[PDB]
Length: 289
Ligand SMILES: CC(C)c1nn(C)cc1-c1nc2ncc(Br)cc2[nH]1
Image 1 (cartoon, rainbow, N blue to C red):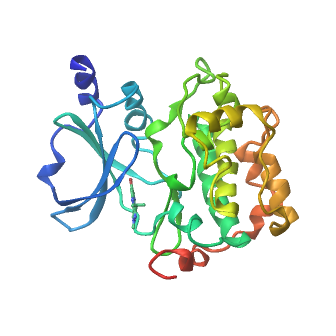
Image 2 (image 1 turned 30 degrees about the vertical axis):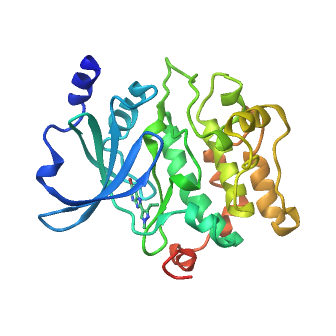
Image 3 (image 1 turned 60 degrees about the vertical axis):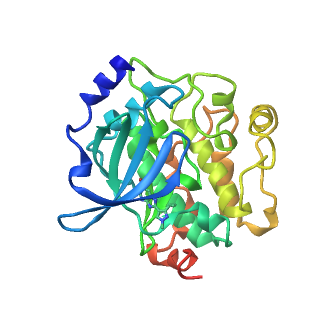
């Protein structure tokens, strides 16, 4: 720790955000710390701040990942990092604020139609081509990780559990990600590539279609056991999805990762043609219904 704080000091911006930020508000909680929002006194713009405790982590060297990998990264479809700091015993990551909030709130309250679902998927997949291109694996994809703007635009967040691969470190080995949405290989402790993200995406479609992931009402521990062992889960209500949507999902939920489609490929699948403008998501959002 003594040494690990010293390292993180050298990757983050020096100084204290409290100097420029006012009026902090907890708005959330992930598995590693909390999420606040805050106002920048000059200008008055809003920012989100992720705050993680250095002493309160399982596997902290993980904490290294977003700050190192995802600094200076930019995309229409990624939530932007501004800076990062250490505040006492915490890591603070200051990020772009998203008004629309999370997709979770939508999938758990309405029935996204096909057009809308495709629009989420294209947004996610655009993002994911470029990420994997660079050998970056998000490793915690799910509706939780999808954030919206006031006008319906989709951006991917929660890179706290992301990973880097290269020519020399080709695949990864650690159990991260979130259990219901984790991939078979990853559970079975295999080396894994980006392709794990693609599986997790599929589970997101089940989220979008059936309102929650497979094996949900189970204990987390047993769900993994199940996810590992059985056949690819399919929809509770099949009769409700287009053949377009099926074939597509059937490219995502593939147990053998070498045959599971690449985002690159998925960016072309006829389904996504159905996607509709950012403004077609708008009425799904809490403050409209
Ligand atoms: C509680 C969360 C889902 C939320 N609600 N609303 C209205 C906005 C948000 C939210 N927007 C966010 N933008 C960036 C980060 Br990092 C976290 C964010 N959380």
